[PDB]
Each structure stands twice: as structure tokens, then as C-alpha cells.
Amino acid sequence: SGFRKMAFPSGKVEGCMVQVTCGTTTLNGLWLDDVVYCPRHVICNPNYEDLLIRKSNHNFLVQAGNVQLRVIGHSMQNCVLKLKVDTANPKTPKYKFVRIQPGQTFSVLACYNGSPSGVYQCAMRPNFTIKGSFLNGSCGSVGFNIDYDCVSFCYMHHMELPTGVHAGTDLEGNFYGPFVDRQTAQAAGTDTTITVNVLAWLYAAVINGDRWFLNRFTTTLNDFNLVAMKYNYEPLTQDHVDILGPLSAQTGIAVLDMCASLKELLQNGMNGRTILGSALLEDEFTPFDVVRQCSGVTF
Amino acid sequence: SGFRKMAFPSGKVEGCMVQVTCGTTTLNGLWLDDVVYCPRHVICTSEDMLNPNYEDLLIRKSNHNFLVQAGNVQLRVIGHSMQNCVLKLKVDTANPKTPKYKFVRIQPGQTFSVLACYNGSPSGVYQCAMRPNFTIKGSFLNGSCGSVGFNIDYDCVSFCYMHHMELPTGVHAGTDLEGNFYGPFVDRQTAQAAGTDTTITVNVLAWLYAAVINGDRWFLNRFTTTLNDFNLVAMKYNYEPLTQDHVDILGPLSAQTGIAVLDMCASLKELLQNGMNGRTILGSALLEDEFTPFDVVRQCSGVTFQ
Ligand SMILES: N#CC1(CS(=O)(=O)N2Cc3ccc(Cl)cc3[C@H](C(=O)Nc3cncc4ccccc34)C2)CC1
Ligand SMILES: N#CC1(CS(=O)(=O)N2Cc3ccc(Cl)cc3[C@H](C(=O)Nc3cncc4ccccc34)C2)CC1
Ligand SMILES: [Cl-]
Image (cartoon, rainbow over all chains, first blue to last red):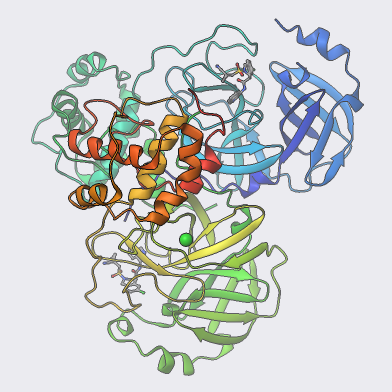
């Protein structure tokens, strides 16, 4: 029993974190085989090709623990800088670079000066920001998931927006969202609630014994989406309904029956009650996260 | 900016997790140097759990009855001893991944990270607090026994908890790494229940200071309170008494924000009376009590968003 915001074990990623220094900027890098990946703003209206051409390999100081790595090459891929080093990381795990979609969750290993500080779980918001916890020096910290024994790196931290939320790129340097890596006027767009995730968390509450919100009613997908659009909830698709199939079979509550419960919660509130110790509807657990935590999958 | 329930990086602990088997029971062990620590109930059957005599059950076992597996490698047990509710299995190989570590016993209100494991393999990491009633609100399934709680302030791991059982209310009970239980619990399936739980007042105040540091002040008021009047009100909402030690401990956060501890207590009294009125504090509609004053200072900026 119990339901916690759970992150993946971070050890395989901790063994890849390094400190990258160029000029007065110090930030974090990800050392995989003989390449260090880091935000291209470590070299800083920036013209990154003009700034980069003026740098020599020895301008980049890379430190792994108490060991200095020597940079032997450099190249830029989108908003990510790739520093070729003479030493392959002996701790390189089995890995992939994957781009995630809004609504998907991942673990963040927050680092400062190449040293891991903490691990937390978060979701890519529908507005492409993440509600992280990052201070100055956290740039280059990474987000990941683990599948079997393989680390899928999905996020690299680049900046904080004026509302306190965060923006970054995939490991190929493509930003999530309409953001740019420059000190300019930027803002997160209006965010929405991840409906499929709220439904997954309601199934998790049922599995753990919280059933007060269940009712005898059902709804159609069309009527549910009309109500959900009114409450700034993301539209629920047939793919979301299919994805929730296993949880619907385990609890005996059809997805549209759980949608009827969610409509009543949106229209009436909780009335002094809580669900899994929360007075808000939680949207940062995917259907897969719920199945994984209620089954004990290991890595 | 931001404020998350943040766990310590788990790598140093992952390299210590092993699987321990005795007969038909399998659970997790912590391998530090040449010793594997695990719950002594690994020697019990489910029948034994009503009134087990651990001394009598243990004397019938030899070293080769304990199977210890680290990854895909079988470790050889060369000795065994019981210390309180933990079994210590001497092995013929010292763990080459043993981090710098200490065994620390914590007090209620303290937080720690839990690395939940099954079959000696880490599954996930989350942040927890030792409740005032000595239980923890964890997330554990069958096979999670032997999973550990820890803190890593600096590069030294301080192990503070080892998981032993789930009580009927769904909450969890365990021991320190010397095998002494937290709370009035026994590693016996007897009618024991968690006592009435209370809110960790000093932690709620720490989290209100975290909200101020992150730029929010809507909940502040023009009042102050005496410590005794605060405690008289707090007890009515099932909040733990606030002591002078707690007031002293909150001194640094008070100095950084410019809000006196008793002035923050007055704000808490008003939040208990009025609720949040559709508002949130650090993304929560409830008063959060699983961040200590130390956790707030570690995570938050040293400069307040005035
Ligand atoms: N709005 C805002 C702020 C960011 S900034 O203006 O100082 N900043 C502009 C900028 C522009 C583009 C790029 Cl790619 C990076 C960056 C940097 C960046 O965000 N860094 C950080 C990242 N994360 C967490 C931070 C917390 C605190 C200060 C910096 C933080 C620097 C003040 C928070
Ligand atoms: N009430 C209750 C329950 C526990 S039990 O009755 O199966 N159980 C009695 C018991 C008594 C004392 C001792 Cl020391 C160990 C133990 C064991 C124990 O707690 N194991 C576990 C531990 N953690 C999380 C579990 C989740 C699910 C099933 C077992 C879980 C076995 C059913 C939840
Ligand atoms: Cl303590």
C-alpha cells in the first residue's frame, strides 16, 4: 500500500555527470562514451556559430569528480554542444536519446558543479514547460526514464521563465516548446491539466482503497470533452481510453465511468475530502507510472 | 525557483542492495563492507509470525541456509548474528561499492529518502518523513522488506531506516540499522495499530518560510502570538506542540525572510481557521509537513524573492 511521487533510481545517471567551464560560465555536462553533452549557452542576441568559432578545445574545462578530462574536439547540434574528450566514460550505461510528448513523466537529477544534488519526478506540461526545482548553476541537469536496463535521456535543462517554471531541450538540442536559448522576453503559455493522468491517479486511488468519488453514472467521450474543455483540461482521446484499459479491467470501473466521477469532481469539488492525501486532482502520474508503482517493477 | 519533494541521488545505496533468501522467504539486504544487514523475520514462516521465538528459530540455521545474491553473483555467508530485530550476515567478499557511511537513529519529523527494492533490485526513490506516531507513509508492496531510508548530506550516506512491515491502516513500520524499531511496534503479527497521527508543526512553518522565499506572502497577517497561545490553538487541529527548540531551529529562515517565528505562527493559526479560500501555497491546497527546516535551506535559494 501507499502511493508516492516516485522517481527512477538515479545511479546510472550520476555516473555520467560532469562540470563544464568556459570563461566565467560553469554548468553541468552529460558524459556518455567519449562525448560530453551540455547547453550551447556555456559559450555565452547570441550568434553561436560566431562565438563557437573563436573557441579552442582547451577553452573548455571539463571536470569528472577530481579528474580533468581533455577536450579534443567540439561541435554544435541545435542548442546542445558536444565536446569530444580523450577518455570514454567507463560508467556509460546502456542508453538512448528519446524525445517525449507533453503529459509524459520523467525523473530529473538536479546537479550543481557536476555534482548530483537531488532527484525528483515531474511531467512535461501541455505548454511544454516543466515545474522543476532549479537554482542558478543547474543548467545541463538531465531528465530520464529507465526501461529494463536502458536509460532513455529525454531532457536537458537550459532556463527558468519569469513565472518560475522551466524550459529545456531533448538530448539532440531541440527545445520543448516555443522557447529560444537567449536572454529575451519569453513566457509560458496558458497551461492545461493532463486529463489521462488525472484518470490514472483516480484508478490508483481506487486500487489503494479511496472510493468515495465513484458513482453509478457513465458519460460519452463527446460529453466528457465538452465538460473538460470548460475546466482547462486537455481533451481525452480514444487512444487515452485504450491506454487506460488495463486499469479499467483491474478495478472494474470503465474509463467513461471514471470520466463521470471526474466530471462530478470538477463541478462540485472534494467537499473537505482528499484523494491519496491531496486536495487537488493530481496530473503528474501516467497510466504506466500507476501500473509500475502498483506492481513493483525493478531496474 | 520551484519547490519539489526532492530525494537524495540513490546511486550510493543502489550499489549496496542485495537479495536475501532463507527457505521460501525472499527479501532485501544492505551489503556494507563484509556484512549484509536484513530484517530478522527472513527466518520466519507466516505461521511463525504470531509468536516467533527468533533465538530458537536462528539456532537451527547454519551459514549455508542463507542465500545472498548480489546482481548475478552468489555471496558466501561465513557467519551470522542477531542484533535486536536485524540479522547481520558475514560474507566472504567486502562490497567494493561500499560508500562512506554512518548508522543514525532519527527523531519524528525528520525526513529521508527511501530506495524501494524487490528481489535485491531497486525499483524507485521517494522522499518520506518519520511521522510523530513513528510510522512512515511509504509506498511498499510485498517483497519490499529490507528496503532502506537514508540521507546523503555531503558524500556520506547516513542510513536511518530499514523496512519491516505494513500495518492494517496501510502505513509502514521499521527499525534503525541497529535493529531497534521506531515506535511501539514488534516484528510479530500481533494486534498493533498506529497511534493517532498529528501534523509536524515545525515542518509546516519551514514550508511557509519556503513559500515566502519563493515569492508568496498572501497568507501573512499583522498579528503575532505567544508560544503558549499558539500551542493551545494548534493542539485543536491535531498539530504537534511547537517547542522552544523548534523556534530556535527556525531562526535562520526567520532572519532570511524578516518574519519572526511567532509572527509566522500567527499566520499558521489563521490558515488553520480560514483554510486557503481557493488559493495554493507552493502548488499545494493542504499545509505540507514533510519538509524540515534543514530541507528548506538545502533546496531554496539563499536570496528571498522580495
Ligand atoms: N526569468 C528568469 C530568470 C533566469 S535569467 O534571466 O537569469 N537567465 C536568462 C537565460 C536565458 C536563456 C538561457 Cl538558455 C538561460 C538563461 C539563464 C537561466 O535561465 N538560468 C537558470 C536556470 N534554471 C534556474 C535558474 C534560477 C535562477 C536563475 C537562473 C536560472 C539566465 C531569473 C530566473
Ligand atoms: N496488515 C497487513 C499486511 C502485512 S502482512 O500481514 O502480510 N505481514 C505481516 C507482518 C507482520 C510483521 C512483520 Cl515484521 C512483517 C510482516 C509482513 C509484512 O508486513 N510485509 C509487507 C511489508 N511492506 C508492505 C507490504 C505490502 C503488502 C503485503 C505485505 C507487506 C507480512 C497485508 C499488508
Ligand atoms: Cl533526527
